[PDB]
Image: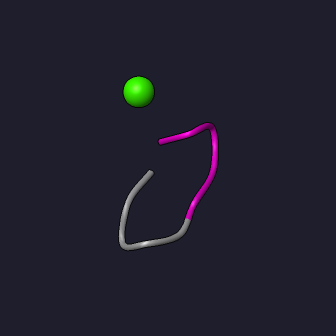
Amino acid sequence: XXASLXXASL
Ligand SMILES: [Ca+2]
Protein backbone atom coordinates (compact mmCIF):
# COMPACT_ATOMS: atom_id res chain seq x y z
CA UNK A 1 0.00 0.00 0.00
CA UNK A 2 1.42 3.59 -0.59
CA ALA A 3 1.44 1.99 -4.09
CA SER A 4 4.58 0.16 -2.83
CA LEU A 5 5.81 -2.93 -1.06
CA UNK A 6 7.74 -2.69 2.13
CA UNK A 7 7.17 -2.37 5.88
CA ALA A 8 5.39 -5.71 5.73
CA SER A 9 2.61 -4.02 3.81
CA LEU A 10 1.25 -3.42 0.34
CA1 LIG B 1 -4.18 3.40 1.10
At 63% across and 50% down in the image, what residue appears?
4
SS majority, magenta: loop
Specify whether 6 is left or right of 9. right
Does 1 sit left or right of 2 as displayed?
left
Quadrant in which ligand 1 is drawn? top left
Give the farthest residue toward the right.
4
Number of numbered markers: 0
Query: Residue 7 at what x, y percent from top left?
Result: 43, 72
Q: Name the colour scheme.
A: one colour
**8 vs 9: above or below:** below
Question: Which range is magenta?
Answer: 1-5
Q: Residue furthest bottom?
A: 7
Kindly indicate the quadrant of the structure image that contains residue 9: bottom left
Residue 7 higher or lower than 2, as above or below: below
Q: Position of residue 6 (x, y in %)?
A: 53, 69
- The answer to whether 1 is drawn above or below residue 6 in the figure is above
Quarter where residue 2 is shown: top right
Q: Residue at x 47, y 42 (%)?
A: 1
Does the magenta portion include 9? no
Residue 2 within the magenta-colored segment of the rendering: yes
